[PDB]
Amino acid sequence: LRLSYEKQDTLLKLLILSMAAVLSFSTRLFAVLRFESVIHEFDPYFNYRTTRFLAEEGFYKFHNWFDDRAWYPLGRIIGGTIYPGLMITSAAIYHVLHFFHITIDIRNVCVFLAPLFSSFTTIVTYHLTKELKDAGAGLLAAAMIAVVPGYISRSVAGSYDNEGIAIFCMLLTYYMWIKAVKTGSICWAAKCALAYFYMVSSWGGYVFLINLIPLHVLVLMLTGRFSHRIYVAYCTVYCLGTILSMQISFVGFQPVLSSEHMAAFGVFGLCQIHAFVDYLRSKLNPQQFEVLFKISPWTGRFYSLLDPSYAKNNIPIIASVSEHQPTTWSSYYFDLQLLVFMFPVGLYYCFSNLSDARIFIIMYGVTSMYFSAVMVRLMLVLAPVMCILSGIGVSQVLSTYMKNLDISKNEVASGMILVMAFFLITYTFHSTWVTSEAYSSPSIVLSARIIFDDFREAYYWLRHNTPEDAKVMSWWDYGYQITAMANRTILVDNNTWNNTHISRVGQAMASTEEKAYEIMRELDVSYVLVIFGGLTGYSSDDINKFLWMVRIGGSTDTGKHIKENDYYTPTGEFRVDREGSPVLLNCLMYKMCYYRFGQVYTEAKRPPGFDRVRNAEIGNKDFELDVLEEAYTTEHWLVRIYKVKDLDNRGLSRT
Amino acid sequence: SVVSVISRFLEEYLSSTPQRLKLLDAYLLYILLTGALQFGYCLLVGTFPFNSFLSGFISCVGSFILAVCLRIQINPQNKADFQGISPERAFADFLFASTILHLVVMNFVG
Amino acid sequence: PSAMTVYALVVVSYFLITGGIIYDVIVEPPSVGSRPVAFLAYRVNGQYIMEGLASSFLFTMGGLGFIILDRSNAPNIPKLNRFLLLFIGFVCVLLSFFMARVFMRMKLPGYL
Amino acid sequence: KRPPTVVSNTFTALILSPLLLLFALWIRIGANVSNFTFAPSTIIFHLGHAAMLGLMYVYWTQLNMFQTLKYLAILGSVTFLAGNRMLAQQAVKRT
Amino acid sequence: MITDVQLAIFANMLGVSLFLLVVLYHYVAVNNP
Amino acid sequence: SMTRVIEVSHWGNIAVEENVDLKHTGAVLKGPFSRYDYQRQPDSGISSIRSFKTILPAAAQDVYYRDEIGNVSTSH
Amino acid sequence: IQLEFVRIDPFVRTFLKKKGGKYSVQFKLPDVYGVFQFKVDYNRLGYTHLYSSTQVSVRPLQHTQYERFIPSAYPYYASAFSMMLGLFIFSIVFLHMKEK
Ligand SMILES: CC(=O)N[C@H]1[C@H](O[C@H]2[C@H](O)[C@@H](NC(C)=O)[C@@H](OP(=O)(O)OP(=O)(O)OC/C=C(\C)CC/C=C(/C)CC/C=C(/C)CC/C=C(/C)CC/C=C(/C)CC/C=C(/C)CC/C=C(/C)CCC=C(C)C)O[C@@H]2CO)O[C@H](CO)[C@@H](O[C@@H]2O[C@H](CO[C@H]3O[C@H](CO[C@H]4O[C@H](CO)[C@@H](O)[C@H](O)[C@@H]4O)[C@@H](O)[C@H](O)[C@@H]3O)[C@@H](O)[C@H](O[C@H]3O[C@H](CO)[C@@H](O)[C@H](O)[C@@H]3O[C@H]3O[C@H](CO)[C@@H](O)[C@H](O)[C@@H]3O[C@H]3O[C@H](CO)[C@@H](O)[C@H](O[C@H]4O[C@H](CO)[C@@H](O)[C@H](O[C@H]5O[C@H](CO)[C@@H](O)[C@H](O)[C@H]5O[C@H]5O[C@H](CO)[C@@H](O)[C@H](O)[C@H]5O)[C@H]4O)[C@@H]3O)[C@@H]2O)[C@@H]1O
Ligand SMILES: *[C@@H]1O[C@H](CO)[C@@H](O[C@@H]2O[C@H](CO)[C@@H](O[C@@H]3O[C@H](CO[C@H]4O[C@H](CO[C@H]5O[C@H](CO)[C@@H](O)[C@H](O)[C@@H]5O)[C@@H](O)[C@H](O[C@H]5O[C@H](CO)[C@@H](O)[C@H](O)[C@@H]5O)[C@@H]4O)[C@@H](O)[C@H](O[C@H]4O[C@H](CO)[C@@H](O)[C@H](O)[C@@H]4O)[C@@H]3O)[C@H](O)[C@H]2NC(C)=O)[C@H](O)[C@H]1NC(C)=O
Ligand SMILES: CCCCCCCCCCCCCC(=O)O[C@H](COC(=O)CCCCCCCCCC)COP(=O)(O)OCC[N+](C)(C)C
Ligand SMILES: CCCCCCCCCCCCCC(=O)O[C@H](COC(=O)CCCCCCCCCC)COP(=O)(O)OCC[N+](C)(C)C
Ligand SMILES: *[C@@H]1O[C@H](CO)[C@@H](O[C@@H]2O[C@H](CO)[C@@H](O)[C@H](O)[C@H]2NC(C)=O)[C@H](O)[C@H]1NC(C)=O
Ligand SMILES: Cc1cnc(NC(=O)c2cc(S(=O)(=O)N(C)C)ccc2N2CCCC2)s1
Ligand SMILES: [Mn+2]
């Protein structure tokens, strides 16, 4: 009342912003209230085990670092193969607290760093949208960003992966570029180069930034809107950004001799070839001017995003992961509700008033949408831009219907604000439900309250009851955990940087017992860890993914007898019952995944030796492993650890 | 046959251009020449140390581009696209960008 | 040129993409129910062609409705035409936002 | 394989020719430093900038990226404050 | 600690209040003098 | 080994936490271990220790049993 | 007695030289990095078997051990420094010049 318009306005903007921030930080906090604060899934177990070694030992003792506890015979270098972004933002955030005598743990400032960086995303989004248009349509973006279900899936409290901290860097870089294009100041461009540098060091998806920018300038150059502002900004950002990007040891000399970063360069030369021509035309006349008138190819990984079928045909490892398939009508709406509708309206409102800044948002939305269409995992990029577009659209509708009200036809004018409020509420509800029920489930804690924590008990056993120089060999999926929890030297890791060693391990499985033993001697493997999952109903059994093992071991020069369409039955169906193919019933994988199993009564009224996951009886009821004596089998038979026997003493053929 | 126009253009650019702006062009030519020499020596011998030549060449392309940016902003004629960017706030910005560029060049070179 | 003639193309591509055309082409799913049931039982991302194109069309309507609404507000429009235009926009908005929700519930029983 | 030392020394001798050419061209244009007035702020700014460049060379031979940055964080701040003062004065004089 | 249900209810209430407040802000914005 | 840490605080309470390394001494196991025999046979694993009971001081408020790797579900 | 420096297959295989009761040999480590194994194996007819194997790890290098100030790259370093000096000179002239 008595408060002036200024004070009221700013106190409302501040209130709403603070509330949005708290909302975002307190909605990705479900996996912690239910189960204790522990990092989850296959990747966050490596980033953690690296940030920890970078905390105690100074940065200079981590830039170069040879980890001889992964790919045992080979050994992988962690110093120059990983983007050191997350580890230096977490080490710094931990060191500052220690300097302030907070003395927090390194496993507690490393779990709550995704939600914290999803509380700074809100502010950056609010500004990135307070630039394209009025503050009025900026807040409406922040709150929607706070509770966007697709983004929340990759940034819950416990997912220490460079994917909930990458979006923040992308937004900051875009805000810097938008400011540079809007104003043209050298300083702003610089402050963008720096953001790109802090983004090329944390997220492997920085090719987007050196491919949307050239696209943006090309469009701002084909329609005839290329002024000196864009020229100055682009050139400065290019130079500084590329030189900064080359610093990182992992990137090396990629920006200058690769076909992924050839866009920026081409647009640079076509920028000059344009500015100079304009200058010449200004100082000349039509008549005289008329008179005068090694590089590597597209790497398969990034090429798979263009051709959506290249993966299936050629790369037999990128198609394995579930989250590598095209998105359906049931993923877009499930993760983004009411945003999908808002996207066309936001586009239309942009296309209505083209400007230097907007022609960038439209390009980003058009590209990101297609990239999300090809692969479900890319939904990271899509949700923020869609949210920004949604913010620019609902607000416009509200603004259009906010002036018609007599206080500021009346019934029709209200009908819109009321419908919009109802849609916003429905969106908040659906977002909370999606975060709660589904996108929040601990990976290593199979639960139905009954808790199955075998994935931890077996690793702890390994870590405590094996010689300090074991060689636990398991599928590349579990490499990150075994080295962070079991603390052994797993033969294959999750980076899959050698497609012959992994093929080797594949061959060692789904083969005759002899061949397997022979392959399990060159690498000096001792223990063997297979995730049975049959007795508990686990969906992702080792047998379930055993097709990938047979299809990635028989695709190299070393082994070809393992050809597919041989483990199948005459009718080509993968049945693991008594009528299955004889070779299948004899491979090392199955032989070590159903050993002394055709006796347990898994179900009330079923044949003794039943399998819950495949709903079929076992074929090889009783057999004795020749080389693999048993060593441990967890209470629920969820993870079985065997141990390769040594060469026979008397030199007999067996064992 | 096409030299008359070139000479006329140069003459024009030697009367219609204010001082304290030609000097910028001279320094720009200097950078363009040091870059040309660098590239020529690279072609003549090839590159054993790649990061050495690459960062002893960017350290010139970046400077050249910063100089051109300063000439653009300083130019009074081009004071419609840039609003509120006084010449002093352009020179200081150029100095800051140059400092970053040189620091990174020093870090990258051997 | 013709800046709008581009927004039309973009909207058409958006309709084709949000109907999972990439999924259809990549992994051909039979557009049939095994009495035919259109929607898949429980898979979070399992698309039959009928579930896809039909769901997408709804989103496109859920966008054109708003565009029609905002366009109607323009002044100097006869009341007879304005009333019809606003009616069409409201019907498209409400109908799309309810049909999509019902479709989602049907595809995934236990929703909300 | 590395090229002969003569082919390297000749070129390093030549790389020094452009800088001399620049001076030979400037002294031709007619640039002078008459506007210099021995003001405190201006001399402090120029000295700071010179020290900053010198540091850019002392971080090559000896220093590591963790001591050079702190020194820059100090010399740059001194250079910035003096520069800003001198730039403000210059701006006022220009008007 | 805090029951999951409690947190969900708090999230719902906060989101609804934040959206109503955003609408109110739009009304105040348009009403500028 | 056992490390007993007793932190005193004049504001509220006193919190004691103890790390316990414990090892089974006699009759080191040899040969394969089989969960099937352990479950379906009472005679199997006589020397094994499934659980032990720790008497607390009758005033403990929130007792957290946690291993190095994470919170352990099983304790009564 | 034959010493073998092996990763999966012997990279190096030399003869230990007797010297004061010890079998000692000195050899440059192979360029390939990774984990390696000293593996002295002495299996002969009518004798005892000898399989001594000590695991060793060969890290690739350190960013502080590459060669610097290479003579071949003298033109690059000088040019970078020339740019740094040029800017300084330019700055002074830019700040203090009287028009004609
Ligand atoms: C499956 C697969 O693939 N996988 C993969 C993996 O993956 C993984 C990853 O990684 C991970 N990650 C992490 C981080 O970890 C994960 O990931 P994730 O999950 O995913 O996560 P993230 O990432 O984060 O996230 C993600 C997300 C996503 C991404 C998202 C996305 C989104 C988006 C959006 C995207 C986008 C897309 C796109 C497409 C874009 C687009 C856009 C748009 C818009 C559209 C549009 C379009 C367009 C085009 C546009 C257009 C526009 C326009 C405008 C138009 C245009 C216009 C125009 C005009 C144009 C123009 C034109 C023109 C210009 C033309 O996970 C995953 C999984 O798990 O990874 C891995 C890695 O690790 C990988 O692997 C890798 O690989 C590689 C390659 O490969 C190779 O191989 C192959 C095969 O074969 C082979 O191999 C095999 C096996 O191995 C065998 O067996 C066989 O036999 C054979 O042999 C081949 O083929 C190929 O070729 C290749 O070769 C490799 O390499 C690697 O390896 C490596 O590594 C490993 C481990 O690490 C190791 O072990 C090994 O050994 C190796 O190592 C190496 O390397 C490293 C690094 O790399 C290092 O460190 C080491 O040491 C080594 O190195 C060495 O070697 C090398 C060889 O290469 C060399 O090179 C080097 O050297 C270098 O470096 C160094 C350092 O480093 C240096 O030193 C040097 O330098 C030096 O020397 C030189 C000589 O010359 C000189 O020069 C210089 O100077 C020096 O320097 C020095 O020195 C001086 C004195 O002297 C001083 O001064 C200084 O200082 C110093 O420095 C250099 O050179 C050495 O030697 C592996 O393996 C896998 O694959
Ligand atoms: C992080 O880690 C912590 C620590 O591990 C963890 O917290 C634990 O969570 C579990 C939940 O699974 C809690 O378990 C509870 O334990 C209660 C205590 O049970 C004891 O007392 C029972 C009562 O017995 C009395 O009465 C009988 C006659 O009825 C009499 O004979 C007795 O002498 C006594 O007077 C007793 O029955 C029970 O016995 C168990 O064990 C024996 C083996 O010795 C077994 O044969 C029995 O069948 C029985 O299982 C035990 O001695 C218990 O009361 C409580 O029960 C509630 O829940 C169950 C379902 O689980 C219901 O069926 C029941 O009706 C009750 O509602 C529950 O079992 C445990 O106390 C926690 N510990 C701590 C320190 O916090 C966290 O969960 C972990 N975090 C996460 C996220 O998981
Ligand atoms: C999912 C994939 C679907 C593919 C769809 C491709 C569309 C994505 C490109 C988005 C670019 C939007 C920018 C844009 O459309 O600019 C508009 C309209 O003017 C033009 O832009 C004309 C050129 C349009 C294409 C320019 C880029 C082409 C592809 C980029 C490499 C500006 O037009 P104006 O110039 O403002 O209008 C003038 C028209 N007169 C009649 C007056 C002459
Ligand atoms: C927001 C922007 C900042 C984001 C920070 C993200 C962290 C990314 C750092 C990744 C490290 C890349 C590799 C690298 O930094 O190189 C390290 C030197 O190591 C370092 O110095 C790391 C310093 C990290 C902070 C740098 C601030 C960047 C400001 C640019 C002016 C090696 O340098 P040195 O080992 O010091 O060189 C020794 C020998 N010389 C003669 C060459 C000096
Ligand atoms: C994982 O296992 C390794 C292998 O033993 C442990 O590394 C040892 O750590 C101790 C620290 O108390 C050092 O004294 C030893 O020298 C290390 N071993 C070797 C071979 O160098 C490591 O500590 C274990 N990780 C844990 C316990 O968290
Ligand atoms: C089985 C796997 C699971 N996850 C994996 N990692 C990638 O697939 C991946 C990695 C990079 S990268 O930047 O790390 N590159 C190594 C420099 C880029 C793109 C990538 N995919 C995005 C779409 C197709 C290729 S492999
Ligand atoms: Mn990751």
Image: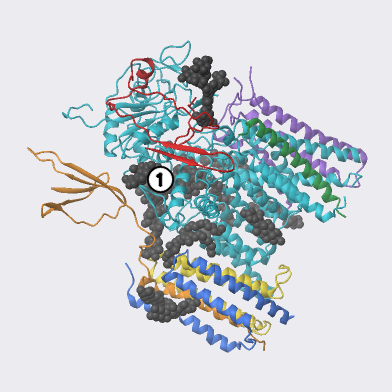
- Report the side of A453 relative to C15 (left or right): left
* Residue F13 location, quadrant: top right
Chain ID for purple: C
Measured from the top left, where is residue G62 in percent x and y? 37, 59
Q: Is mark 1 within 8 Å of ligand 1?
A: yes
* Residue C102 location, quadrant: top right
Chain ID for red: F
Measured from the top left, where is residue A102 in percent x and y? 55, 50
Residue at the (65%, 28%) spot, across then down: C50
- Per the rendering, the colour in which chain G appears is orange
State the residue in front, G54 or A350: G54
SS class, disc 1: loop
Measured from the top left, where is residue F47 in percent x and y? 32, 22
Q: Is residue A492 above or below residue A168?
A: above
- Report the side of G65 relative to B61 (left or right): left
State the residue in front, A167 or B6: A167
Chain ID for cyan: A
Q: Residues within 10 Å of mark 1 (few under 14, many from 20)?
A: few
- Per the rendering, the colour in which chain E appears is green
Pointer 1 indicates a residue of which chain? A
Q: How many marks?
A: 1
- Per the rendering, the colour in which chain D appears is blue
- Report the side of G46 relative to A465 (left or right): left
* Residue C97 location, quadrant: top right
Q: Which residue is tagged 1?
A: A497
Chain ID for yellow: B
Q: Is residue B84 above or below residue A55?
A: below
